[PDB]
Image: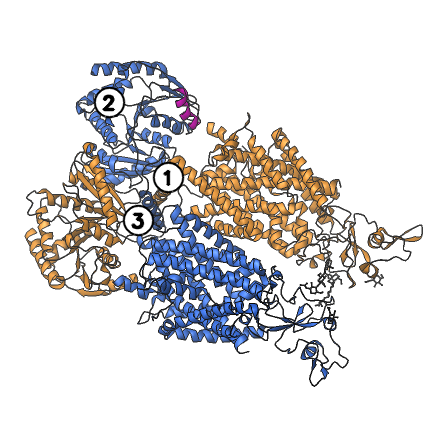
Chain colours: A blue, B orange
């Protein structure tokens, strides 16, 4: 009907989509099903079940499948987010997680896939040599034939990948036919089990490669000649004065049915772990037994490796890997974000069900002794899982070989394409050599490097030792795929819109934890090494991207960190639950281009206590075309002054023609979007009456109006020459805060920040509210600093200039009276707080008409007449 | 002569210095020495030597001393940088590494100190019970006696810490007297070793708590009666047909000298590991032996714990811990930055030399069987190391007890002070409860919590099991102390001036790696838990600091990240090794407040390709007091447009009185210090001749002058309405870069940034140099980008207006002819490149006199007459 492929899509298809079909079943389901079902299912699942007991084997398969299922959910969350690139899964992961995580996952998954092509070559060799056509001799035969087979497969992939594309379907056919034959044998074996017997001497297990009859004697022509096994246990071979060993004269050889019915119920026997160390004779705890020992013969089938749980999880994990292959055909899809998630999750559920079913079936169908036989012995040298099959074990012996060769081809085509895809992205420099492609878009040097690493793997010619390394690399890939999603969801990374029905970051975090535990339990030895390798590749990719875009290595790294923080800061709720003053100190520069008020900087330092944001801005009057040198010089001056007063922050000079216009630009333009200020700190215009130009107060009131309009808070410090330095202290004093009807946020917050500095540490706080005891106490209760309160009420007209404003606020959603009431306020404040070290004091808004600006300044001067040090405060905003 | 103490200085002594003597020996040396010499030296060092073999014991002691020495170097680097606060080591660590690392190290060191108070109480109890005043019965005796002793010590430190301060000198005296007695015994054991014999049955060692003579029969009144050991190996006790077991009738009991001479040469025997598992009889591979077996008796000295290498390193590590106690008496110092590093490093060298010498002395003076005896058995119940002393083992057994109870007092004074110091800092909120102090400043709740944790430790009543947890916590403390230093030195963290003669960041990195390996080798399953607890405390402290200073949790967290990156960015070389265009796109806003040139944003996105910094700036002509609504509206519009054109960056609007002045402020004030732009991208003023207002081109040339004076690059795009979009592409085309005489760097770097985008991907590049050939080829080969070259030389007059300015540059570091030559340049440029897709072109500077601005604009206009899409480029800077 239709011809399809299971391979990956490298740069060949991505460059095609960059220059400018199949559904869910044939597109993202069958490739994943063909790539999860590996050699393990046929060569090591039985041994794992036997060695672990059905309970712990079920636990193993469940833990592995849960790691891989949470990784599938994270990978589907990656697939749905944004447009899915036409390339393989690597391109999806890159465009979804940034080039850093993309390169880390790419290299770890690549080493995984290479060592998988090695494991599959070892498995095909083991099947060909042990079962198809018959210690260290076996290992060296495997080394030699595996190297020959790898050279052949490398040539196959290099010359004729089109034929791999054509016969991927035949490979999947073989896989599914083998699995269905396993199930048909398992079901048939219930009523009619096959006649595969096993010789067993007492409770010690015998081999069957050389023995023919499970009897201590055979009778040819009614002659009690002793069986061949007598020769394999007694150095007499004739029974004539047979000097037989200890355990042989006592016990009984029995031909136990090796495949009992699924209804026979052997599961009660093998429901428990064995974990016997290396070289122990395999015992069935059912048959009779003597107690003498010693006769360690050559025919006793032995445990071939010191097995443990932590070892079994590693040996079995490479049978569930392959879910990144689910999306290796993502370019040829109709609805990517719909086909990929459902396809991957359904394929993983299918394979998990197949494994969890075969575990229990093997528990109930194969004898508890033939399971622990890791090389298909004791059954006349037949595949143990093969004994469960309807036609013959040869269908499995052939299907497994063809499937393992097909998976080797798939992973020897998927590894170099992935490596050249990582190379052409210029993510990592040194891999550029591997970008070299063939004419039709096929890798040349990547294939050679893949072959070299696969050979390095094959040098360890044992599946039982190649599986842990493969599992560790794939576990690192899955751990990063889960962690990147969890991180980008928590921190609210920009362009992280996971349009998935079931993805929650708790799933990805639980997956990261599960698979990290798997890594470390399997082998912390390899786990630390893999984590460090992946971390180094990650940091190196980040450094290279920095040096590529910003131009410097470490400079650009910090630059990128700052840019990313500010960007993340933009796509958020611009309001904050608490109000904190981020100061903009408007320093006044004299004609000497020297700060006319260092006390402004000292007080800003005292207010922020060296933490937070402090932008010190200043305007130089003149033309920028002919002042840039003076601008840089004054900037160095202000930076030295800031560093001298321990102010941590930045400086900005604007050369403008009009000081008023310069300030009106500074107030509204300082800071990058997100890092805006919300308070403007000014110095009082001393000697405003003594200036015949009157431009002092005009500029001051213009700045006040601009700050009020911009909705920023305002702190005008008056008599700033008396504000203390850093080195001196106050022995004792009182900050008297006069919190009028309005702006309780600032008037209550500032003295708390100020008393928190060492200079103002030894002073007390006195709130002389003029605008109730419990409500004010709550704020003090939260600030956790005792602050004596007191109320001094006066007439409304006395507070007219305030309450008028209040009315204007309410509706929003005479001069002689204002002056003589400012003098009444003066009388109270001076009589109560003359000796205060710092008097905070609320401000009225400037008049709506610009004519009363002189009157406004006279009002302020009166309101502050006689006080040693005043901090005029105005809220202005929301808070 | 003088009285001192070795305890810590908490917040009580720091608030004194905030409100407002000893040298090196008595100030930093003796406290560190008295705190490193713990109980291990006396109770488990001999056992470790025995069960490890002198070689591996030396390796273990060397690794521990190596980690502690590298951590001492990092801590000295912390101590020298800046002023040393008057508080304990915690205040130094905090002020040097920030509150996050300060709190993490504080809590890890505090858990360390609590479990150290527990280990020292267990050790004092073990010495009292086993050696001074005599399986699970012993464990329960230790539990109950340790709980009683802990409640006593807690009461002592709560009531009467002054007497502990007084007797710290007596405790140190005890330590030194004990160590000198050990050395004097080792020396006297050269000629005349002591008479401590051990009964040994062949090569199997016997106990001696109940035996009297190491003979099978003693003779009272000429009667060869059987010895008591007969009563312990033979259930006859009469010799009248005695039925003795297997091993006893064959072998011989011998009185082997237990302490041979130092020159005896027994070291050759115990120079190898034993690592025997649990319950194994201790075997001396020197004496004769039969081969019979079976006699498992009660008098065989048995290995009391399953020793291993990874267990031994953990059991021994808590004898090198305590280096932070060196600077726990820093407030009472004369020259802190000189006294702390020298004192700490000399103390660690002294203790390391003592340990490395005692390892070899124990190897070569004590029989290889008495060393592996972990409870001083087989020597009539005396301390193993005690047997090596000049007067008697009693001096050592009393000195060790007094030293260990003194160190218990020390750690129950040092742990709660450190906890109240971490509480009063309000670094971690929930610990605020423990901030309460006594009248004289002594912790009350902190002492109770320390008592609770120490009791939890004591409930595991075994030094051998408490030591790994203690060692893991101190290892985590040292790991953070080495990693924060490595990071702050590499990343150029502000205020990180390590004024030390020998501190190089490679040392701290090596220490970090060393004792990361130590953690994991000791117990990876404990170590991951410790790392995760420390990481959670670290991130929670960072979050609380963000919420405190900025006002919000996650928003403020990204804010802190951005501010810290910018600060770190300031104190660096302001130049960059590479130049990369960081664009300021100047969008001109029409009277309708709509973006007059979206193609500006499109081309900016194509130039930066979604990465880098793009500040889109625009000026709104008008008065700010009555326009802020329009400002927010236009800002939202420009932000939506930036998102529409795939531009990632920030938007700044300035409401200015004069458009020219607004742009002159924007060009010099955009961006925070460090994140400054370097290029200004402008749109050409189309229809300047048809708009009879002379201010259009005036404003344009003013912006050009401002850019040139600011030393920023300039990119004027002309005919921008026909520039492409993001969706469309080019089939085939040539980006022709016409590098006129100067400013080649940008003119060549731009077309590669352009062609690296999907739009311009399918175009070619042509460098039409006018004013060698191989010089370009080498630059392009270094950049790994190839293009097509062509050279078109012309007459000098034609480029006169250029060359003039070039000469004015070389000297630094008419108009009608200019127009007739711009027309000649036009001839050639069109004849070669008329049908190009994008013609880059260098620019001449604006005239010096602002009168010829009409002439300059006519020059430009004719130079670009007839070209489809021109990108005028001007260097301006260094590059
Ligand atoms: C296969 O047969 C051998 C030999 O009969 C079994 O070894 C023996 O197993 C029995 C288990 O009942 C052991 O008995 C136990 O002995 C210990 C020590 O004496 C005693 O404390 C227990 O209460 C129990 O009686 C016996 O020692 C052991 N023989 C040895 C170790 O030499 C073997 O267990 C059989 N395999 C299976 C799977 O049952
Ligand atoms: C302390 O004395 C006991 C009692 O003899 C020693 O145990 C025995 O040590 C001999 C050492 O030669 C062991 O012989 C060995 O047998 C193995 C197995 O055939 C062989 O491969 C070796 O070459 C060697 O001949 C013997 O098995 C062992 N008997 C036991 C353990 O029951 C013990 O070794 C002595 N300890 C030391 C430290 O010397
Ligand atoms: C072996 O078989 C014989 C006869 O079938 C039986 O008497 C004997 O008990 C068996 N041996 C054991 C150990 O059960
Ligand atoms: C025990 O000592 C006697 C005499 O001293 C000697 O004959 C005998 O061989 C010794 N036994 C062993 C096992 O060496």
The reply to whether the C-beta atoms of the residues labelled 1 and 2 are less than 8 Å apart is no
**Residue that extends furthest to the bottom in the rendered view of this protein:** A221
**Which span is picked out in magenta?**
A771-788
Q: Would residue A98 be seen by someone viewing this image from the given angle?
A: no
Looking at the image, residue A366 lies above or below residue A695: below
* Quadrant of the image containing the N terminus of chain B: top right
Q: Which residue is mark 1?
A: B556
Q: Which residue is mark 3?
A: B575
Q: Circle 2 sits in a helix, a strand or a loop, which is it?
A: loop
At label 3, counting other C-alpha atoms closer than 10 Å, the crowd grade (few under 14, some 14-19, many 20 or more) is: few
Q: Which residue is mark 2?
A: A687
Which corner quadrant of the figure contains ligand 2? bottom right
B644 displayed left or right of B177: left
Of the two numbered discs 1 and 2 in the rendering, the one whose residue sits closer to the viewer: 1
Membership of B253 in magenta stretch: no
Of the two numbered discs 1 and 3 in the rendering, the one whose residue sits closer to the viewer: 1
Q: Circle 1 sits in a helix, a strand or a loop, which is it?
A: helix
Q: Provide the chain ID for the residue under circle 3.
A: B
Distance between the alpha carbons at the discs numbered 1 and 3: 30 Å
Distance between the alpha carbons at the discs numbered 1 and 2: 41 Å
């Amino acid at each position: 009907m239709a011809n399809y492929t299971n391979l990956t899509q490298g740069a060949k298809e991505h460059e095609e989509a960059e220059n400018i079909q199949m559904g869910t079943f044939m597109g993202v389901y069958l490739p994943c099903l063909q790539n999860i079902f590996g050699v393990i299912l046929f060569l090591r699942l039985t041994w794992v079940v036997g060695t672990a007991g059905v309970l712990q084997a079920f636990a193993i398969v469940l833990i592995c499948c849960c790691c891989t299922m949470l990784t599938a959910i994270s990978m589907s969350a990656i697939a749905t987010n944004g447009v899915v690139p036409a390339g393989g899964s690597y391109f999806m992961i890159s465009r979804a997680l940034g080039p850093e995580f993309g390169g880390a996952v790419g290299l770890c998954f690549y080493l995984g896939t290479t060592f998988a092509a090695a494991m599959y070559i070892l498995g095909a060799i083991e099947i060909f040599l042990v079962y198809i056509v018959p210690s260290a001799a076996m290992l060296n035969n495997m080394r030699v034939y595996g190297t020959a087979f790898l050279v052949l497969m490398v040539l196959v992939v290099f010359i004729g990948v089109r034929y791999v594309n054509k016969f991927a379907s035949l490979f999947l056919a073989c896989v599914i036919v083998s699995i269905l034959a396993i199930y048909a044998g398992a079901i048939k074996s219930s009523f009619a089990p096959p006649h595969f017997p096993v010789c067993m001497l007492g409770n010690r297990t015998l081999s069957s490669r050389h023995i023919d009859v499970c009897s201590k004697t055979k009778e040819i022509n009614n002659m009690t000649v002793p069986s061949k096994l007598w020769g394999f246990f007694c150095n007499s071979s004739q029974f004539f004065n047979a000097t037989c060993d200890e355990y042989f004269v006592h016990n009984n050889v029995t031909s136990i049915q090796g495949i009992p019915g699924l209804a026979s119920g052997i599961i009660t026997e093998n429901l428990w772990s064995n974990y016997l160390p290396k070289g122990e004779i395999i015992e069935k705890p059912s048959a009779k037994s003597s107690d003498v020992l010693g006769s360690l013969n050559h025919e006793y089938v032995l445990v071939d490796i010191t097995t443990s749980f932590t070892l079994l999880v590693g040996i079995f994990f490479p049978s569930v890997t392959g879910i990144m292959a689910g999306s290796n055909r993502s370019g040829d899809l109709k609805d990517a974000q719909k086909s990929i998630p459902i396809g991957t999750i359904l394929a993983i559920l299918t394979t998990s069900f197949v494994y969890l079913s075969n575990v229990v079936l093997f528990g109930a169908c194969i004898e508890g002794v033939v399971l622990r036989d890791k090389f298909g012995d004791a059954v006349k040298g037949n595949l143990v899982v093969g004994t469960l099959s309807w036609p013959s074990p040869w269908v499995i012996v052939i299907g497994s070989f063809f499937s393992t060769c097909g998976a080797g081809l798939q992973s020897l085509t998927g590894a170099p394409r992935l490596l050249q895809a990582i190379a052409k992205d210029n993510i990592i420099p040194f891999l550029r050599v591997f970008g070299h492609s063939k004419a039709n878009g096929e890798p040349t040097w990547a294939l050679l490097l893949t072959a070299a690493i696969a050979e390095l793997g094959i040098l360890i010619a044992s599946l039982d030792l190649v599986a842990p390394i493969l599992s560790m690399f794939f576990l690192m890939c899955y751990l990063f795929v889960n962690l990147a999603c969890a991180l980008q969801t928590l921190l609210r990374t920009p362009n992280w819109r996971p349009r998935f029905r079931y993805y929650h970051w708790a799933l990805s975090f639980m997956g990261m934890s599960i698979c990290l535990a798997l890594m470390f339990i399997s082998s912390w030895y390899y786990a630390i090494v893999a984590m460090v390798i992946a971390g180094m590749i990650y940091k190196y990719i980040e450094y290279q991207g920095a040096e590529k875009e910003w131009g410097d290595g470490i400079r650009g790294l910090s630059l990128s960190a700052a840019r990313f923080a500010l960007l993340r800061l933009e796509e958020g709720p611009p309001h904050t639950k608490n109000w904190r003053p981020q100061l903009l100190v408007l320093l006044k520069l004299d004609e000497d281009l020297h700060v006319k008020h260092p006390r402004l900087l000292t007080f800003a330092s005292q207010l922020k206590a060296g933490k937070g944001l402090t932008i010190v801005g200043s305007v130089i009057v003149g033309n920028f075309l002919e002042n840039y040198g003076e601008a840089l010089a004054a900037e160095q001056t202000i930076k030295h002054l800031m560093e001298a007063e321990k102010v941590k922050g930045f400086c900005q000079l604007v050369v403008a023609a009009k000081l008023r216009e310069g300030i009106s630009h500074l107030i509204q333009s300082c800071g990058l979007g997100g890092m805006k200020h919300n308070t403007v700190v000014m110095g009082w215009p001393n000697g405003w009456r003594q200036s015949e130009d009157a431009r002092a107060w005009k500029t001051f009131i213009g700045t006040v109006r601009v700050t009020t309009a911009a909705h920023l808070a305002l702190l005008v410090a008056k008599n700033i020459s008396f504000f203390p330095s850093n080195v001196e202290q106050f022995s004792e004093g009182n900050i008297d805060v006069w919190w009028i009807v309005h702006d309780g946020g600032m008037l209550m917050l500032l003295p708390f920040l100020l008393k928190q500095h060492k200079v103002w540490r030894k002073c007390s706080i006195r709130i002389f509210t003029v605008a109730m005891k419990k409500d004010l106490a709550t704020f003090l209760y939260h600030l956790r600093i005792e602050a004596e309160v007191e109320v001094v009420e006066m007439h409304d007209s006395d507070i007219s200039a305030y309450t008028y404003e209040r009315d204007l606020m309410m509706e929003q959603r005479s001069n002689v009276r204002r002056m003589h009431t400012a003098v009444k306020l003066n009388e109270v404040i001076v009589n109560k707080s003359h000796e205060a070290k710092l008097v905070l004091l609320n401000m009225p808004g400037p008049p709506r008409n610009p004519e009363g600006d002189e009157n406004y300044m006279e009002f302020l001067e009166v309101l502050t007449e006689g006080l040693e040090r005043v901090l005029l405060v105005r809220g202005g905003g929301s808070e």
